[PDB]
Amino acid sequence: TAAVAIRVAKKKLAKPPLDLHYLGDRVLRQPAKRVSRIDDELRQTIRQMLQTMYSADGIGLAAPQVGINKQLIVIDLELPPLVLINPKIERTAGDLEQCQEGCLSIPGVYLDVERPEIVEVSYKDENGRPQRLVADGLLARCIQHEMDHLNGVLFVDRVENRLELNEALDKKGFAVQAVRPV
Ligand SMILES: CCCCC[C@H](CC(=O)NO)C(=O)N[C@H](C(=O)N1CCC[C@H]1CO)C(C)C
Ligand SMILES: [Br-]
Ligand SMILES: [Zn+2]
Image 1: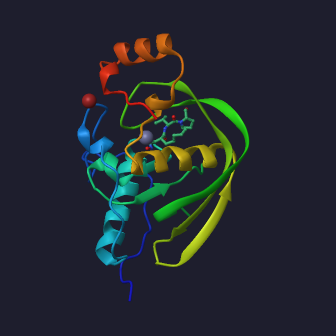
Image 2: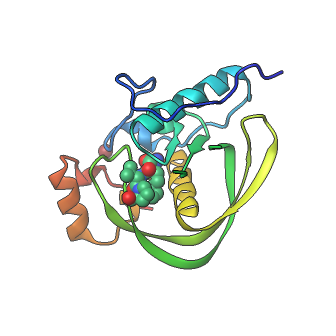
């Protein structure tokens, strides 16, 4: 019986509860383990992910980014957050759209990424109930970005412009050698 409620305030925190890892760190390149059990301990991790996300001003956060090797994502675009546990992309749709992306694991780097406009995903929610969602726009983009993290893929991997990739990584102190093919 769940006893942990997910009721997280959106606040800057002096000391975020979970620690980010950044491009080059091998934790970002490890395909995430399935979540075995959706219990109250997992809900507290969810709370801490949301607190960490909000404090860093993100709209999504995947557990590998904070060194937790689990198929777990939290998303909140709104000015009730979405929790995806063991998600699967069922298919994509629409046209391929190129938009600017950033990542909390690659601070300061903004580059164009082409993705399908629309995504359908199946997942278990924070109460263990199976759900399915179809998304478009920024939500579809964030979902695909986060699912990338669960598979060890980072947005820089999808960037086609070598000049802009190298310049942006250079200006922010990251190594192009940390980039991987898709
Ligand atoms: C766009 C798809 C990426 C969404 C998720 C990321 C956070 C992250 O790294 N998740 O793994 C985010 O909030 N990124 C922000 C971001 O790039 N955004 C937010 C909406 C538009 C886009 C560029 O401004 C930056 C400001 C941290
Ligand atoms: Br590397
Ligand atoms: Zn990211």
